Amino acid sequence: MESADLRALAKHLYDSYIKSFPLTKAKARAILTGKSPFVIYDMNSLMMGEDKIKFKHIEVAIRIFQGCQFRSVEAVQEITEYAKSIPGFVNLDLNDQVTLLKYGVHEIIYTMLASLMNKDGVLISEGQGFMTREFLKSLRKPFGDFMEPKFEFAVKFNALELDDSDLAIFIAVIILSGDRPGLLNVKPIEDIQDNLLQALELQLKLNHPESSQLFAKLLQKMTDLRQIVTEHVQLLQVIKKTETLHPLLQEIYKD
Amino acid sequence: MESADLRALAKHLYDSYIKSFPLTKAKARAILTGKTTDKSPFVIYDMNSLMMGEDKIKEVAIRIFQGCQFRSVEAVQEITEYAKSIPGFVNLDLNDQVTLLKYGVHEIIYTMLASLMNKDGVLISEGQGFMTREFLKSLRKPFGDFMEPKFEFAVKFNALELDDSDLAIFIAVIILSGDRPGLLNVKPIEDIQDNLLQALELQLKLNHPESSQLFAKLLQKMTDLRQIVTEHVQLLQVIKKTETDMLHPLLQEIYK
Ligand SMILES: COc1cc(COc2cc(C(=O)O)ccc2-c2nn(C(=O)c3c(Cl)cccc3C(F)(F)F)c3ccc(Cl)cc23)cc(OC)c1
Ligand SMILES: COc1cc(COc2cc(C(=O)O)ccc2-c2nn(C(=O)c3c(Cl)cccc3C(F)(F)F)c3ccc(Cl)cc23)cc(OC)c1
Image 1 (cartoon, rainbow over the protein chains, first blue to last red):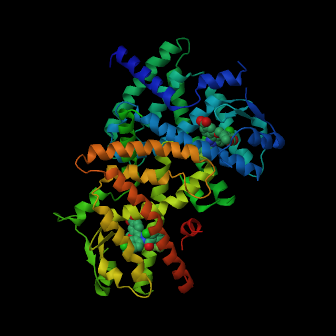
Image 2 (image 1 turned 180 degrees about the vertical axis):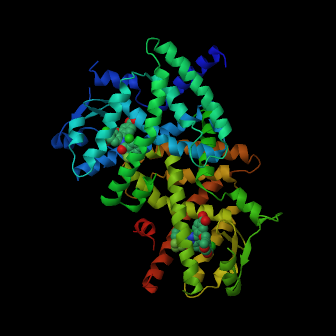
């Protein structure tokens, strides 16, 4: 509705995003730009890194892969809590709430991973570690090709130069997608997303006055996310199908 | 912890329990206590009705036993999804997550099995069926003694008259037990349980105001289940020594 109302909606989402996510993009950027993390750049520094920082995840490539999984499962919970703060979400049909989270979390994880990345690597363990891109890119069998597309996405995504207040609204828009399979009541979902989209458009105008058609460009990225997530789940399928784990542990990571 | 925060924890757990478990106690009671033309189960009380039931919905004792196992495996899956929603669980050491599930799932299954039960039998196939206590109690060799202790517990547990919003918190409390064998970091688990216990205590006072010392009574039940689970695995052990030709990989790993 009114501009005052969209601004209030943007502020509400920002305040909630700050409480929901441990490491903001602003904090990550301060770290990546040297403005201090333990650096993992090869096999020996990896072994020291587990010695040094307290990894809760514990072949080298598998351990790293298991580390991605562990953090993603935490991210899913963090995003799930975030969604409850999106005005109207908790009033949706419970099955639709589940459906929106089920298909949304992977796109949001990918999006938010870009905040922890630059062209040279990725922050881990709330910023205590930094794993270099070239070291990840050089892992064996399929694992190297599993890590690198995330960086290829993140470098393009980061050229938009979004900040946390932009991302708080963007994340909400992805959750409130009325085309997820199996939704029971599309209408209030699109009505919410319509509101979030108005708030994002106003947010990008005020926060990036010089950035022409940034709204449109961000929407284009949101579409990309669908196919890159689909290729991700396909690679996830094969790595799980070949490189075997306890049944209880496998059940934790089934989703 | 502040009341508003404990109430918020109760709503989060209740909402997540509804999302993770397809047949709630509220639905089970609606089916069992009827009033219904649409929710009424087909009743299995003997061999003939069993054979008709398969039409409607490998000695009987084995078929029934494998039917439990399949369902118990699904329950494990449901319980694992539930646990991931308990605030703080997925942030624990991965080995401890596995350990909490390994020792927790059986106690929760029995707990939730009570919801599908009355003194006369148990709902099956998401409530389409109802198998009588006496028919199970009469199965052969050890299988007859295998079903009956579930009923003995359930009759005592159901007298507490808990509803699903209570059970959601109770179930979480069970998972977050810092005394499971082999845990590496007891303290953060105990810290989660402290909050869950505070939340259970407020939930039970508000939701059962006239039910004196229900918190204490509910905790006493949580201890029993530990031995009731032991009697189950001790029975299970013998079946393995007897029925050499028969467990799901998930159930196999949970045991030992
Ligand atoms: C402790 O040890 C570590 C820790 C990490 C940290 O990673 C991440 C951190 C965050 C965060 O904090 O917000 C978010 C996503 C990742 C990550 N996920 N991932 C997947 O594959 C993935 C994705 Cl995108 C989406 C859904 C599911 C999955 C998964 F389930 F299948 F995992 C990555 C692949 C490559 C990279 Cl570089 C990062 C991620 C990374 C690490 O090694 C690189 C080791
Ligand atoms: C479709 O066909 C059916 C279906 C059932 C349905 O049962 C159950 C349903 C549920 C549920 O839906 O949440 C939960 C537990 C049981 C059940 N398990 N069980 C075991 O023994 C057992 C247990 Cl507890 C734990 C681990 C492993 C096992 C097992 F692997 F070793 F089995 C029971 C023993 C007696 C009773 Cl009465 C119920 C259960 C029951 C049925 O016959 C009774 C036939």
